[PDB]
Length: 410
Image (cartoon, rainbow, N blue to C red; front, side, top):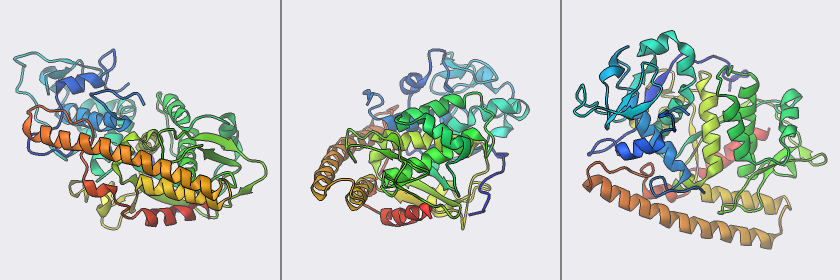
């Protein structure tokens, strides 16, 4: 940890496309169509058959970027004849995606699997910088999901008396609010981009992610607060989980002595149902977009994402992983230990977590198995969620990540 953190404005605008397998990019035109806005814009538990989970849109949008963006970078007129999956751009500014001609003007673009793009090769983005910067958090979010072996990474940073001054008043203005609402409002505030490293929006987003995470893992709770603040949920690891911002006058307040940083990813596929992890993953992309962030350890990203200058390196910042169930269980263990619930209410809670994780393993397991089968056999099949492997359900290195995160209060 540099004592200052990541103060450098962003100067490199790299994009990493989604890995795909034997039958190409696991999307089609019906799925891509479904992601667009009323105005045809790709840049603007409510499940659907097409997108079963919250984490579905994240994956499916990474395929939309990978299909549509890397193919127009060739120049100023690329958009006139460019088409992919039956879609074409409306203008050089990539405002909207509409139906292509068929036959098209040129041969349709072929997405490439797990491939890097320098987005500054787009002449318009090289000259009108503010219009790349405003799209880049979306594009970075895709890039990071594609580079991750499992679920989405979080940017996790604490610093000496981090919630104070106007940042304190800001958190107090949100007393009793839901975490996901807070995240959506900040996304909302960032639309008109000007996000400077260490500015107000930046410091809010970083402090929100780590306040939340440290409550998610149980080390921050009502007996152990950051400048009074903590998130709470009545349930833990369960369908009903809902994190509310609370404030305490009279309980222990941590004394952060130094700056702390970690990248933390979700190992287990239940990340797909976790709205708070996903909302934290979205802020993470806005936070990372505005700066040059820590360089990833190579072992933290898939093979095709290694050794990208400014992004990944031998010796980079490690990516810690969390099995979500293990973490729910550990959170609960922290709550019993803090005297926040009885030892018997701890068991009830563990059992409702274990029980919910059972229904999610099975629902995702079947989505996986159907998707895998259909991807290999049905041409032009649209996968509904990022591919995973059954081993992602083990704890893995969860305990290592919990031990590191517990030091973030010191």
